[PDB]
Length: 330
Image (cartoon, rainbow, N blue to C red; front, side, top):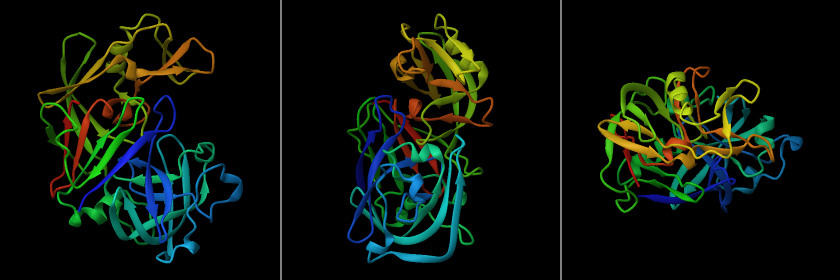
């Protein structure tokens, strides 16, 4: 089997991407944030505290003839941005782009933190990291990809995120029309539960490539590119007037600037992020200070190849017995 679904930016900055997902019988379609940095499929629901729902579409398990309470199971997750959610668990039929999994754990939120409530466009998350990170207790549950894998034509999914435009998540096949050149594959460590890999270096604009190992994660659920402070300083030093602002929370730059590109290495191959992809717009409405799309990871503990980086590439998440990642230009 295969599946193919369009993913759409939630706003004009590409802060996140939403993908329609069919849950239950008859189908209830919710727009989920596909997150290769986590491993829980959770939704706003008829069980979510009413004051914490503000415009999201909810899953109502009582209206699904295939929903079953997973008795005794609870979940609770905290994300790198400080947001969180928790609740109980049903199993139900879940379909993405024509690919159907029966018995998928659908984690129903009883509580969500304010950032989720405040984002009316995201109805939940669909985790695509390794199932060892799934938070369901006392019986850990499998991701949608893990449940689908054996049925897929090939044990892979691909992320093709757009810049200021829709893109595609495919399951079970690699669309050879969706990229240019060849796909370069690179090793993955699953020891932390992430799609963790080592970039071979970077360049700023037309500058020379610096060969240096940068361990990080391919994370579709993180907006920006978070890299070591040395790398980030080298980038922003090429932008007149750019500075790190403790009050804003990262590097800012004059909105009048033209940003240089940023290149990252994948083995001997190179992915070029155009400068425009690094512009996240005014820090507040009407400001002439703009927020940068490349930020330091120093306070995170891990480097994160988020959407800024991934949207410059066609990305293969290869879930073979030994997982690997593939990157191609497009």
